Image: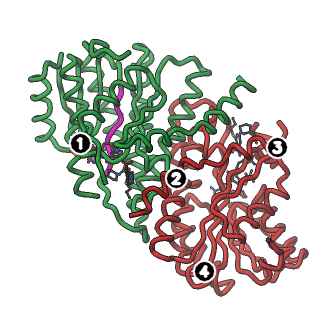
Chain colours: A green, B red
């Protein structure tokens, strides 16, 4: 049911687009002829991405460098991006703070930083974007992980942040349903992807290029969840039908 | 296989014990003859709770009033509590910041406060308690909710904080398994309970007295999860076998 034309002329923010899945998403949106605003801390890598976007046939491509540790930057970023495109059709929240695979001892500053960059900054970006997304009847895409659905050692702070995104966005999705806010929320559950970050930090990784295209497709098709894993078995097990029943058994009782 | 005597003479911290489930847990541990240290913001209420604990037959009962927004208080409390009892056998993390069941608009300070009180403070308390819990081969009890497993409207910040507890504690449980740290982690998934807080905020809720005894029982029996709900049907639906399989799929390795 997805057609690349669905993205032609669309106004899209992609966070964490200097590298990995983010950079790949920005390139796919460009090949489809969308207006893209990209961000990361690194100005020079961002520049290279923006020019390559214009080479692929993007309607427009821009960058705004900054840290998502700074909540005022998150706020002002959406404002300038919106100004550049004259509005916003899709918000792709994808960035993450640097983490290493390590046992948890006492790094409370690291738990805080992850919670700030990976979680609160997503909430702050959403609040800022919500008036524009309401106008266009837009979409919010939240890039999560299997580590944000299930428990693995070595990723406690990261898992906590990804789990937090599920609780927050999944609850606001129920609120938008009742409030009749026509803004879709897509949560992406990915397994290990072949990004240079992941490859160095860590089985069989899945291709970054297809992963990127799937995230966009899911968002465009207004899906609640998107699954992307190198295994058939893992994808079958990602789904939580009891959760759905539990959730739906409340709504079909009060609403 | 639970016996009340398993708690006799045991050293236990109970957070959020001025009211609700927390206060009830503190009373149950008191009837079993345990050493209890209780905490909350409310000093005059904690006093009344402590004296009632000693009336029920607690080996000792003490309190330390303070706010879990303050991370240094969280740190200081565990040392102070650990000094009072000469060690720690069980850590019951139960407190929550005040929330109302409203639609989310733009209250970022509220998302932050919930994340700090309901989540960060639990992590800070754990880090502080871990050396003592290692000595006794202790237990950490994390009080969560169904709203921390499943999605409901009107509780976004609260859900985020409860979901975060699951990811963090469930991952550290895997780390303690590989590191061979003999400290158990119990996550409690509760439905509505008949506490004044809940009866004011939001409805056939489950009794707080039995809820309180179950949390303790689960912790004592070193269970990974504890379920407590007024519905048998809901209870059946809480288990996630696919998650378990995905988790163990990795383990080997
Ligand atoms: N790769 C996998 O195996 C995998 C698996 C499951 C889920 N995911 C999820 O997929 C998403 C993309 O990950 P990825 O593999 O593409 O990782 P990545 O290559 O490390 O990309 C992270 C991006 O965030 C940026 N960033 C870092 N710190 C930042 C900060 N403080 N403020 C703003 N931006 C910051 C990075 O660039 P700068 O350094 O230029 O700031 C980069 O553009 C993440 O949400 C991740 O959790 C990935
Ligand atoms: N009752 C339910 O329907 C329900 C449902 C699911 C899960 N649960 C879980 O069960 C636990 C107990 O809930 P409850 O209904 O018994 O709630 P409660 O009566 O409101 O008790 C929460 C406790 O936390 C303390 N507290 C509040 N803000 C604090 C702060 N900033 N710093 C330190 N302590 C603070 C309160 O004391 P002060 O104001 O004196 O500080 C109180 O003793 C929670 O983890 C809750 O999520 C309950
Ligand atoms: C012990 C590794 C935990 S991290 C992690 N584990 C995942 N598992 C466990 C290993 C096998 C794997 C198999 C699969 O693809 O089905 C599924 C899947 C995704 C992540 C993840 O999002 N990793 C981050 C870490 C920080 C940097 C970004 C990437
Ligand atoms: C829409 C209400 C969401 S709050 C909430 N809902 C729960 N549900 C939804 C209603 C029906 C209920 C039925 C059940 O027992 O199976 C299951 C269960 C627990 C909570 C909860 O943790 N409550 C907190 C809120 C803040 C104050 C402290 C208590």
Specify the label residue B137 is tagged with: 4
Residue at 67 percent across and 48 percent down: it is B145
Residue at 44 percent across and 39 percent down: it is A235
Name the residue tied to disc 3.
B205
Please rate how many residues cluster around mark 3, counting C-alpha atoms within 10 Å: few if below 14, some from 14 to 19, many from 20.
some
Task: Tell me which segment is drawn in magenta.
Answer: A91-97
Please rate how many residues cluster around mark 1, counting C-alpha atoms within 10 Å: few if below 14, some from 14 to 19, many from 20.
many
Quadrant placement of the N terminus of chain B: bottom right
Specify the label residue B170 is tagged with: none
- Place of residue A162 in the rendered image (x, y in percent of width and height, measured from the top left): 44, 46
- Horizontal relation, residue A178 to residue A24: left or right: right
Q: Which type of secondary structure does the marked residue at label 1 adopt?
A: helix
Image quadrant where residue A41 sits: top left
A217 vs B200: above or below: above
Name the residue tied to disc 2.
B245
Front position among marks 1 and 2: 2
- Place of residue A70 in the rendered image (x, y in percent of width and height, measured from the top left): 33, 45
Please rate how many residues cluster around mark 4, counting C-alpha atoms within 10 Å: few if below 14, some from 14 to 19, many from 20.
some
Chain name for mark 3 = B
Q: Which type of secondary structure does the marked residue at label 3 adopt?
A: loop
Q: Are marks 4 and 2 in contact (CB under 8 Å)?
A: no
- Place of residue A74 in the rendered image (x, y in percent of width and height, measured from the top left): 34, 37
Looking at marks 4 and 3 on the same chain, the residue that comes earlier in the sequence is marked by 4
Rounded to the nearest angstrom, the CA distance separating label 4 from label 2 is: 27 Å
Q: Which type of secondary structure does the marked residue at label 2 adopt?
A: helix
Q: Quadrant of ligand 1?
A: top left
Looking at marks 4 and 2 on the same chain, the residue that comes earlier in the sequence is marked by 4
Whether callout 3 and callout 1 share a subunit is answered: no
Q: Is mark 3 within 8 Å of ligand 2?
A: yes
Residue at 25 percent across and 46 percent down: it is A194
Name the residue tied to disc 1.
A20
Whether callout 3 and callout 2 share a subunit is answered: yes
């Amino acid at each position: 049911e997805f057609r690349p034309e669905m993205l032609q002329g669309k106004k899209v923010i992609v966070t964490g687009a200097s590298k990995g899945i983010g950079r790949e998403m920005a390139y796919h949106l460009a090949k489809m002829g969308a207006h893209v605003v990209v961000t990361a801390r690194s100005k020079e890598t961002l520049q290279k991405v923006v020019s390559h976007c214009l080479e692929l046939g993007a309607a427009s491509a821009h960058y705004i460098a900054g840290t998502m540790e700074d909540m005022t930057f998150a706020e002002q970023f959406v404002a300038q991006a919106g100004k550049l495109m004259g509005g916003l059709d899709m918000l792709i929240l994808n960035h993450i703070t640097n983490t290493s695979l390590n046992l948890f001892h006492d790094d409370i500053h690291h738990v805080r930083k992850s919670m700030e960059v990976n979680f609160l900054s997503y909430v702050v970006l959403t609040v800022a974007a919500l008036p524009m997304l309401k106008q266009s009847n837009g979409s919010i895409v939240v890039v999560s992980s299997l580590a944000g659905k299930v428990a693995y050692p070595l990723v406690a702070a990261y898992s906590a942040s990804k789990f937090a995104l599920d609780g927050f966005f999944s609850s606001i999705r129920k609120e938008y349903s009742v409030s009749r806010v026509n803004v879709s929320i897509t949560l992406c559950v990915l397994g290990l992807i072949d990004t240079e970050t992941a490859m160095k930090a860590v089985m069989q990784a899945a291709p970054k290029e297809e992963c990127a295209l799937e995230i966009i497709k899911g968002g465009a098709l207004r899906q609640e969840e998107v699954y992307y894993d190198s295994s058939r078995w893992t994808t079958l097990l990602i789904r939580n039908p009891s959760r759905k029943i539990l959730e739906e058994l409340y709504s079909t009782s009060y609403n």
